[PDB]
Amino acid sequence: TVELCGRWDARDVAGGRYRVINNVWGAETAQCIEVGLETGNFTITRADHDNGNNVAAYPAIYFGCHWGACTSNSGLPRRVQELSDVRTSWTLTPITTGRWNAAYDIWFSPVTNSGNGYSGGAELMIWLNWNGGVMPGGSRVATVELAGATWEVWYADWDWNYIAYRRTTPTTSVSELDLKAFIDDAVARGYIRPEWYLHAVETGFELWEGGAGLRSADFSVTVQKL
């Protein structure tokens, strides 16, 4: 394993299929993650965050293209209308202190270049676990049954459309979760357009305060085109 403490530190893992990023994008407080290079599994070993109501960091593992940095042979970006199946697995280890969530962050945009971000596109989050009273951005607009569970749907109209599906009860693992079910729901609500591109599928922990001890493991993403 290797411990990464740099603000924008990263490592390609699993033969280049995925990439792990320390990603302390919202603060200057220290954070380190210890990463297994073959699997991408990681534990947050240090997290000095105490950021109030703003997210301090999002250590994560991803498949696809994150702000122009793409993993090896992901097949992304690809238009939503050209996707037939999108599945993912993940196992998280929660802690009982701090303010954080365990959530997928999935990015879409109308164009193929993601170097300047996803303005005019959408951010689709799937919250599986959390602690400390944190809540998604925007407002709760519905509660829906999807992919075997029930989820609150939160929406915010920002620079990009923010959509967060928050499980009604927390969980610590998913196996071959049908991400297309969530994409289809967001398309039906008008939050994502079929002509937009899916750029990246990421999962990790948004941290507001603390976070040391959280562990990410068993990550996998597969995408099948029509």
Image: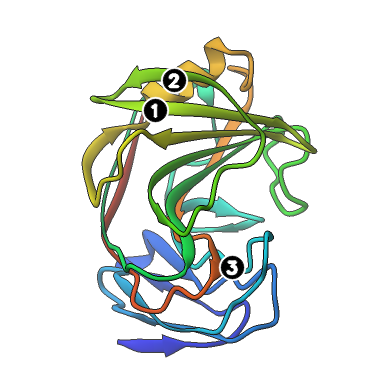
For badge 3, the amino acid type reads Ala
Residue shown at the point (43%, 44%) measured from the top left: 127
| 71 and 138: which is toward the camera | 138
| 168 and 66: which is toward the camera | 168
Q: Picture coordinates of residue 5 (x, y %)?
A: 52, 88
For badge 2, the amino acid type reads Thr
Mark 2–mark 1 CB contact (< 8 Å): yes
Badge 2: residue crowd in 10 Å (few <14, some 14–19, many ≥20):
some
Q: Which residue is mark 2?
A: 143
User: Mark 1 or 3, which is nearer the eye?
Assistant: 1
Q: Which residue is mark 1?
A: 151
Is 2 drawn above or below residue 68 in the view shown? below
Residue shown at the point (59%, 86%) measured from the top left: 30
Q: Picture coordinates of residue 58 (x, y %)?
A: 54, 64
User: Mark 3 or 2, which is nearer the eye?
Assistant: 2
Q: CA distance from mark 3 to mark 2?
A: 28 Å
Q: Which residue is mark 3?
A: 57
Q: Is residue 225 visible?
A: no
